Image (spheres, helix red, strand yellow):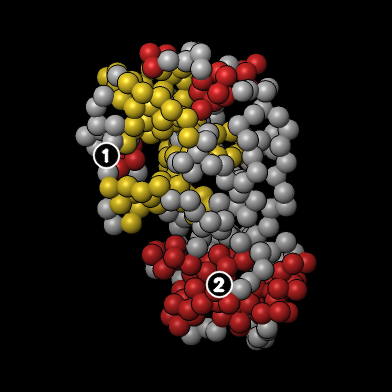
Protein backbone atom coordinates (compact mmCIF):
# COMPACT_ATOMS: atom_id res chain seq x y z
CA UNK A 1 0.00 0.00 0.00
CA UNK A 2 0.96 3.63 0.47
CA UNK A 3 0.20 6.35 -2.08
CA UNK A 4 2.78 8.45 -3.94
CA UNK A 5 2.73 10.96 -6.78
CA UNK A 6 4.53 8.72 -9.27
CA UNK A 7 5.78 9.62 -12.70
CA UNK A 8 6.13 7.29 -15.66
CA UNK A 9 9.55 5.73 -16.26
CA UNK A 10 11.47 8.13 -18.50
CA UNK A 11 13.95 5.89 -20.38
CA UNK A 12 12.01 5.93 -23.65
CA UNK A 13 11.96 9.77 -23.77
CA UNK A 14 15.53 10.22 -22.48
CA UNK A 15 16.48 8.30 -25.57
CA UNK A 16 15.10 11.26 -27.50
CA UNK A 17 16.27 14.55 -25.94
CA UNK A 18 18.84 16.47 -28.01
CA UNK A 19 20.28 19.98 -27.76
CA UNK A 20 19.43 22.55 -30.44
CA UNK A 21 21.54 25.70 -30.76
CA UNK A 22 20.75 28.57 -33.09
CA UNK A 23 22.84 31.69 -32.99
CA UNK A 24 23.57 32.28 -29.31
CA UNK A 25 20.43 30.56 -28.00
CA UNK A 26 20.50 26.92 -26.85
CA UNK A 27 17.58 24.82 -25.71
CA UNK A 28 16.38 21.23 -25.81
CA UNK A 29 14.77 19.40 -28.70
CA UNK A 30 12.84 16.17 -29.30
CA UNK A 31 14.47 13.87 -31.89
CA UNK A 32 11.90 11.40 -33.21
CA UNK A 33 12.31 9.59 -36.54
CA UNK A 34 14.23 11.99 -38.85
CA UNK A 35 12.74 15.18 -37.35
CA UNK A 36 13.66 17.37 -34.36
CA UNK A 37 10.99 19.41 -32.57
CA UNK A 38 11.85 22.54 -30.59
CA UNK A 39 10.35 25.93 -29.63
CA UNK A 40 10.70 28.47 -32.38
CA UNK A 41 12.09 31.14 -30.09
CA UNK A 42 15.34 29.25 -30.31
CA UNK A 43 15.88 31.68 -33.21
CA UNK A 44 15.31 34.79 -31.08
CA UNK A 45 17.82 36.81 -29.13
CA UNK A 46 16.64 38.53 -25.94
CA UNK A 47 15.78 41.89 -27.45
CA UNK A 48 14.02 39.70 -30.04
CA UNK A 49 11.48 38.44 -27.50
CA UNK A 50 10.12 41.92 -26.71
CA UNK A 51 8.27 41.78 -30.06
CA UNK A 52 9.33 39.00 -32.47
CA UNK A 53 8.16 38.55 -36.06
CA UNK A 54 8.89 34.91 -36.64
CA UNK A 55 8.50 34.67 -40.43
CA UNK A 56 10.80 37.70 -40.76
CA UNK A 57 13.45 36.27 -38.43
CA UNK A 58 13.19 32.71 -39.77
CA UNK A 59 13.86 34.09 -43.24
CA UNK A 60 17.37 35.15 -42.14
CA UNK A 61 17.99 31.54 -41.00
CA UNK A 62 19.11 28.63 -43.21
CA UNK A 63 19.72 24.93 -42.57
CA UNK A 64 23.37 25.37 -41.45
CA UNK A 65 22.50 27.90 -38.73
CA UNK A 66 21.02 25.16 -36.51
CA UNK A 67 23.27 22.86 -34.43
CA UNK A 68 21.51 19.67 -33.39
CA UNK A 69 23.66 17.73 -30.92
CA UNK A 70 22.74 14.30 -29.51
CA UNK A 71 25.04 13.19 -26.76
CA UNK A 72 28.44 13.80 -28.34
CA UNK A 73 27.46 13.39 -32.06
CA UNK A 74 26.19 16.12 -34.42
CA UNK A 75 23.06 15.67 -36.51
CA UNK A 76 23.07 17.03 -40.06
CA UNK A 77 20.13 19.40 -40.74
CA UNK A 78 18.67 19.17 -44.27
CA UNK A 79 15.39 20.99 -43.79
CA UNK A 80 13.58 23.47 -41.54
CA UNK A 81 9.96 24.48 -41.20
CA UNK A 82 7.72 26.18 -38.62
CA UNK A 83 4.41 24.63 -37.52
CA UNK A 84 2.66 27.20 -35.35
CA UNK A 85 5.17 27.70 -32.51
CA UNK A 86 7.36 24.60 -33.02
CA UNK A 87 10.30 24.46 -35.37
CA UNK A 88 10.80 21.12 -37.12
CA UNK A 89 14.35 20.30 -38.21
CA UNK A 90 14.61 17.55 -40.80
CA UNK A 91 17.89 15.70 -40.24
CA UNK A 92 19.71 13.02 -42.22
CA UNK A 93 19.51 10.14 -39.71
CA UNK A 94 16.57 8.53 -37.93
CA UNK A 95 16.77 8.19 -34.22
CA UNK A 96 17.57 4.50 -33.72
CA UNK A 97 15.90 4.92 -30.30
CA UNK A 98 12.57 6.24 -31.58
CA UNK A 99 9.77 4.61 -29.55
CA UNK A 100 6.24 3.87 -30.62
CA UNK A 101 4.74 7.30 -30.14
CA UNK A 102 1.83 9.64 -30.74
CA UNK A 103 1.16 13.36 -30.41
CA UNK A 104 -1.94 14.02 -28.32
CA UNK A 105 -3.48 17.23 -27.05
CA UNK A 106 -4.58 16.60 -23.48
CA UNK A 107 -7.58 18.29 -21.79
CA UNK A 108 -7.47 20.37 -18.59
CA UNK A 109 -7.31 18.37 -15.38
CA UNK A 110 -5.51 15.43 -16.97
CA UNK A 111 -1.95 14.82 -15.78
CA UNK A 112 1.38 13.93 -17.40
CA UNK A 113 5.09 13.50 -16.63
CA UNK A 114 7.65 16.21 -17.42
CA UNK A 115 11.27 15.24 -18.04
CA UNK A 116 13.16 18.40 -17.10
CA UNK A 117 16.31 18.90 -19.16
CA UNK A 118 19.17 21.37 -19.73
CA UNK A 119 21.40 21.27 -22.82
CA UNK A 120 19.81 18.09 -24.14
CA UNK A 121 20.66 16.17 -20.90
CA UNK A 122 17.90 15.13 -18.45
CA UNK A 123 18.13 16.17 -14.85
CA UNK A 124 14.81 15.12 -13.45
CA UNK A 125 11.31 13.74 -13.86
CA UNK A 126 8.09 14.81 -12.09
CA UNK A 127 4.30 14.40 -12.43
CA UNK A 128 2.10 17.45 -12.92
CA UNK A 129 -1.39 18.42 -14.06
CA UNK A 130 -2.68 20.71 -16.80
CA UNK A 131 -4.36 23.38 -14.66
CA UNK A 132 -7.88 24.53 -15.64
CA UNK A 133 -6.23 27.77 -16.89
CA UNK A 134 -3.83 25.82 -19.16
CA UNK A 135 -0.77 26.88 -17.17
CA UNK A 136 1.26 24.37 -15.20
CA UNK A 137 3.21 24.70 -11.96
CA UNK A 138 6.51 23.13 -12.92
CA UNK A 139 10.24 23.31 -12.21
CA UNK A 140 11.98 25.07 -15.13
CA UNK A 141 15.30 26.92 -14.95
CA UNK A 142 16.75 28.70 -17.99
CA UNK A 143 17.59 26.29 -20.78
CA UNK A 144 14.84 23.97 -19.62
CA UNK A 145 12.87 25.19 -22.65
CA UNK A 146 11.83 22.40 -24.98
CA UNK A 147 11.48 19.88 -22.14
CA UNK A 148 8.56 17.61 -22.93
CA UNK A 149 5.76 15.99 -21.00
CA UNK A 150 4.24 12.66 -21.87
CA UNK A 151 2.11 9.70 -20.86
CA UNK A 152 3.04 6.06 -21.56
CA UNK A 153 0.50 3.31 -22.39
CA UNK A 154 2.09 -0.16 -22.41
CA UNK A 155 4.82 0.53 -25.00
CA UNK A 156 3.59 3.77 -26.64
CA UNK A 157 4.68 7.29 -25.63
CA UNK A 158 1.99 9.97 -26.07
CA UNK A 159 3.77 13.32 -26.11
CA UNK A 160 1.49 16.11 -24.95
CA UNK A 161 3.51 19.13 -23.76
CA UNK A 162 6.56 21.10 -24.80
CA UNK A 163 7.70 23.91 -22.55
CA UNK A 164 8.01 27.39 -24.04
CA UNK A 165 7.96 30.10 -21.41
CA UNK A 166 7.53 31.20 -17.82
CA UNK A 167 4.96 33.88 -17.17
CA UNK A 168 5.78 36.80 -14.87
CA UNK A 169 3.67 35.05 -12.19
CA UNK A 170 6.09 32.11 -12.00
CA UNK A 171 3.75 29.59 -13.66
CA UNK A 172 4.82 28.04 -16.98
CA UNK A 173 3.30 27.62 -20.44
CA UNK A 174 3.78 25.58 -23.58
CA UNK A 175 2.30 23.77 -26.53
CA UNK A 176 1.31 20.42 -27.91
CA UNK A 177 3.86 18.90 -30.28
CA UNK A 178 2.00 20.48 -33.19
CA UNK A 179 2.86 23.94 -31.83
CA UNK A 180 -0.51 25.15 -30.57
CA UNK A 181 -0.34 26.73 -27.15
CA UNK A 182 -2.21 25.37 -24.24
CA UNK A 183 -4.28 28.43 -23.49
CA UNK A 184 -4.29 32.00 -24.68
CA UNK A 185 -0.55 32.57 -24.50
CA UNK A 186 1.93 33.56 -27.19
CA UNK A 187 5.71 33.21 -27.46
CA UNK A 188 6.41 36.89 -26.79
CA UNK A 189 8.03 38.41 -23.70
CA UNK A 190 5.10 40.61 -22.73
CA UNK A 191 2.79 40.80 -19.73
CA UNK A 192 0.33 37.91 -20.17
CA UNK A 193 -2.51 37.13 -17.77
CA UNK A 194 -3.55 33.71 -16.63
CA UNK A 195 -7.15 33.62 -15.52
CA UNK A 196 -8.61 32.23 -12.34
CA UNK A 197 -6.99 28.94 -11.29
CA UNK A 198 -9.81 26.64 -10.16
CA UNK A 199 -9.50 23.22 -8.57
CA UNK A 200 -9.98 19.98 -10.51
CA UNK A 201 -12.94 18.69 -8.55
CA UNK A 202 -13.10 15.16 -9.97
CA UNK A 203 -9.41 14.65 -9.23
CA UNK A 204 -9.94 15.61 -5.59
CA UNK A 205 -12.75 13.09 -5.36
CA UNK A 206 -10.52 10.39 -6.91
CA UNK A 207 -7.86 11.21 -4.30
CA UNK A 208 -10.32 10.94 -1.39
CA UNK A 209 -11.21 7.51 -2.77
CA UNK A 210 -7.51 6.65 -2.92
CA UNK A 211 -7.36 7.76 0.72
CA UNK A 212 -10.13 5.41 1.78
CA UNK A 213 -8.38 2.56 -0.10
CA UNK A 214 -5.30 3.16 2.10
CA UNK A 215 -7.13 3.41 5.46
CA UNK A 216 -7.56 7.23 5.85
CA UNK A 217 -11.30 7.40 6.53
CA UNK A 218 -11.85 10.15 9.11
CA UNK A 219 -13.36 12.66 6.66
CA UNK A 220 -16.26 10.34 5.80
CA UNK A 221 -19.21 12.28 7.23
CA UNK A 222 -22.78 11.02 7.67
CA UNK A 223 -24.40 13.16 4.96
CA UNK A 224 -25.19 12.86 1.29
CA UNK A 225 -25.89 15.65 -1.23
CA UNK A 226 -27.04 16.51 -4.74
CA UNK A 227 -24.98 17.38 -7.80
CA UNK A 228 -26.64 20.83 -7.80
CA UNK A 229 -26.01 21.64 -4.14
CA UNK A 230 -22.46 20.39 -4.56
CA UNK A 231 -21.83 22.60 -7.58
CA UNK A 232 -23.23 25.51 -5.57
CA UNK A 233 -20.67 24.87 -2.88
CA UNK A 234 -17.96 24.17 -5.47
CA UNK A 235 -18.43 27.44 -7.32
CA UNK A 236 -18.26 29.42 -4.11
CA UNK A 237 -14.81 27.89 -3.54
CA UNK A 238 -13.33 27.97 -7.08
CA UNK A 239 -13.85 24.30 -7.80
CA UNK A 240 -14.47 23.05 -11.33
CA UNK A 241 -18.17 22.10 -11.42
CA UNK A 242 -19.06 18.43 -11.39
CA UNK A 243 -20.81 16.73 -14.33
CA UNK A 244 -22.49 13.34 -14.72
CA UNK A 245 -19.51 12.30 -16.85
CA UNK A 246 -17.31 12.96 -13.84
CA UNK A 247 -19.69 10.88 -11.73
CA UNK A 248 -19.48 8.06 -14.28
CA UNK A 249 -15.67 8.08 -14.38
CA UNK A 250 -15.61 7.62 -10.61
CA UNK A 251 -17.74 4.48 -11.00
CA UNK A 252 -14.86 2.03 -10.63
CA UNK A 253 -13.65 3.76 -7.42
CA UNK A 254 -17.20 4.00 -6.08
CA UNK A 255 -17.81 0.27 -6.52
CA UNK A 256 -14.41 -0.71 -5.15
CA UNK A 257 -14.89 1.26 -1.94
CA UNK A 258 -18.61 0.78 -1.32
CA UNK A 259 -19.03 4.56 -1.08
CA UNK A 260 -21.53 6.25 -3.38
CA UNK A 261 -20.16 9.16 -5.39
CA UNK A 262 -22.68 11.64 -4.02
CA UNK A 263 -21.88 10.61 -0.45
CA UNK A 264 -18.27 11.39 -1.31
CA UNK A 265 -19.43 14.77 -2.62
CA UNK A 266 -21.13 15.41 0.73
CA UNK A 267 -17.90 14.68 2.62
CA UNK A 268 -15.88 16.89 0.24
CA UNK A 269 -18.36 19.74 0.68
CA UNK A 270 -17.98 19.39 4.44
CA UNK A 271 -14.18 19.53 4.09
CA UNK A 272 -14.60 22.67 1.99
CA UNK A 273 -16.91 24.30 4.55
CA UNK A 274 -14.81 23.48 7.61
CA UNK A 275 -11.14 23.07 6.69
CA UNK A 276 -9.22 20.07 7.96
CA UNK A 277 -8.82 21.20 11.61
CA UNK A 278 -5.14 20.22 11.44
CA UNK A 279 -5.62 16.63 10.39
CA UNK A 280 -3.94 15.36 7.25
CA UNK A 281 -5.19 13.12 4.48
CA UNK A 282 -2.59 10.80 3.00
CA UNK A 283 -0.05 12.94 4.82
CA UNK A 284 -1.22 16.13 3.07
CA UNK A 285 -2.61 19.12 4.94
CA UNK A 286 -4.57 20.21 1.85
CA UNK A 287 -6.75 18.69 -0.85
CA UNK A 288 -4.78 17.25 -3.79
CA UNK A 289 -6.00 17.65 -7.37
CA UNK A 290 -3.06 16.28 -9.42
CA UNK A 291 -4.32 12.67 -9.60
CA UNK A 292 -6.89 11.67 -12.17
CA UNK A 293 -9.28 8.78 -11.51
CA UNK A 294 -7.20 6.79 -13.98
CA UNK A 295 -4.08 7.67 -11.98
CA UNK A 296 -5.65 6.30 -8.80
CA UNK A 297 -6.77 3.06 -10.44
CA UNK A 298 -3.36 2.47 -12.05
CA UNK A 299 -1.57 2.93 -8.74
CA UNK A 300 -4.14 0.91 -6.74
Specify which label sits upstream in the sequence, 1 or 2.
1
Could you tell me how many numbered marks the image carries?
A: 2
Residue 193 rendering spot, x and y as whole percentages: 73, 41
Residue 59 rendering spot, x and y as whole percentages: 51, 17
- Contact between marks 1 and 2 (CB within 8 A): the answer is no
| Point 45% across, 41% down: residue | 177
Q: Is residue 265 above or below residue 292?
A: below
| Tag 1 secondary structure | loop
Report the quarter where the C terminus lies: bottom left
- How crowded is the residue under tag 2: few (<14 C-alpha within 10 Å), some, or many (20+)? some
| Label 1, label 2: how far apart the Cα atoms are | 35 Å
Q: Is residue 166 above or below residue 287?
A: above
| Point 71% across, 29% down: residue | 190
Report the quarter where the N terminus lies: bottom left
- How crowded is the residue under tag 1: few (<14 C-alpha within 10 Å), some, or many (20+)? some
**Is 61 positioned to the left or the right of 199 in the image?**
left
Residue of label 2? 246
Q: Is residue 192 above or below residue 245?
A: above
| Point 38% across, 13% down: residue | 64
Q: Residue furthest right?
A: 236
**Is 251 positioned to the left or the right of 269 in the image?**
left
State whether residue 72 appears in this view. no
Residue of label 1? 98
Residue 248 rendering spot, x and y as whole percentages: 51, 77
Q: Is residue 287 above or below residue 128?
A: below
> Looking at the rendering, which quadrant does residue 120 occupy?
top left
| Tag 2 secondary structure | helix
Residue 8 rendering spot, x and y as whole percentages: 37, 51
| Point 48% across, 67% down: residue | 293
> Looking at the rendering, which quadrant does residue 46 occupy?
top right
Label of residue 191 in the image = none
State whether residue 251 appears in this view. yes
Amino acid sequence: SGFRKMAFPSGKVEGCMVQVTCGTTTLNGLWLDDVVYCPRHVICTSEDMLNPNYEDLLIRKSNHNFLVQAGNVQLRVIGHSMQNCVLKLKVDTANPKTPKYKFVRIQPGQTFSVLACYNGSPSGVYQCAMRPNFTIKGSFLNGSCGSVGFNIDYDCVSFCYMHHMELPTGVHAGTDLEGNFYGPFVDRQTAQAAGTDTTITVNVLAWLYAAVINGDRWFLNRFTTTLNDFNLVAMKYNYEPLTQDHVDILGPLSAQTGIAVLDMCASLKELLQNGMNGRTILGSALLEDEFTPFDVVRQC
